[PDB]
Amino acid sequence: SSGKVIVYGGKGALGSAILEFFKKNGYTVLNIDLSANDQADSNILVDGNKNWTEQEQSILEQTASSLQGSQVDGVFCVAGGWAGGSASSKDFVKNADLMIKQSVWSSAIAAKLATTHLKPGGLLQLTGAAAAMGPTPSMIGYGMAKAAVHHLTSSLAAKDSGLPDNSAVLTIMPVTLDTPMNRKWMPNADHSSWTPLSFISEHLLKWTTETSSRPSSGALLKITTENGTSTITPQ
Amino acid sequence: SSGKVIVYGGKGALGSAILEFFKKNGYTVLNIDLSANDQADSNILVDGNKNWTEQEQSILEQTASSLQGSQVDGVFCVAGGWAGGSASSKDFVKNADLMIKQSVWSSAIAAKLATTHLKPGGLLQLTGAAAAMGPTPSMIGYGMAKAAVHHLTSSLAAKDSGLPDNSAVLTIMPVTLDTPMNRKWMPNADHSSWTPLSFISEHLLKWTTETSSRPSSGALLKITTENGTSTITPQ
Image (cartoon, rainbow over all chains, first blue to last red; front, side, top):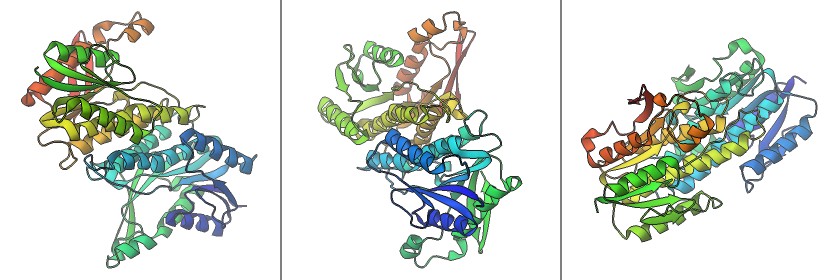
């Protein structure tokens, strides 16, 4: 009863952590992903075989059916994976396509959901990429896709973008997150530079409940950890 | 027989002007577009209903059959149209989809054509968007797509991107071009602030034949005209 929030990508490591955290803190949580999270109060099913507009329609219809006359306090989008390759790579385009579908499609639909269901003064959070702040010749598609998300962020923060009054959009860019996969493939790394998922969940709850604790709307927030201490620096 | 160049978007106002100017200067020109330009030496037709990878394979195979192991002196991409809308617009996603396909898909395939056929020291030219240098709340999809093209430019210019040795990539951003459509919809505008298509065609030929006349590789070139004089300003 503390409120409602949408987690787009609730099946992932960070997404599941965020969903669990808000639930523990009294919020009703709606998950939007390729499969259901049996811990969520509501599950919106995404069909990966459908195109962009088909996905938008289905996700919007399902979310509206679930919310009825309620609005949400926040929409958190953390969906998407990775695929690299330079222009000379055999799969340069193939992977570029996958990256648009994974980062751009989701971010845009999350934004559409916010213009429709986010309460005035609410929070929309998107996921960018620290690497996209500069050239990315070894992973051009990923770079392009994320740069589009960064631009989307700037357009949404601007006047008459469609977001509700007094709301804010924040885009996170963590350098290294502590996940099961990172522990497996880099088993001997120094975790003193790894950002705990709880650092993110905690900040999302803070920004959701206290508007005065928020960085400027449209901020691209680079998150780093050194000597066990995490820091958020607007770029 | 001055050489060979590829014009992706040869049916457009600017694309046709470029094609005509290079043909007039002794070049063999290959056109890539939705329909054929009867003045081109070769025509590569694209099916807009095919997906990104299908389009890539189709364009690459047709171009290779037309070149037969030969290289090109330049690849010029000016394809793409426009669709607007803020995030609250009914067609926000629909148009974002159209804009990614029109600007991003084409720019990436043009880049692929360059890694495969552009001569060392050759030129790859892409088309960005001056408006995308800042927030675009009234045309979010267009802004996202063009921002991706701007980032793609920075990645391609970097070492090991896949482009040939000593080649350069330049991306143009004209504020206003003198086209038939602009003359029709803005009939009483002052043309002293309109950039003549010839200005662009002339610079492409110069940059193609004289490497020392080129701005830095990776440059985003804003083009403005005032009192009849045109100026190129790197961002």
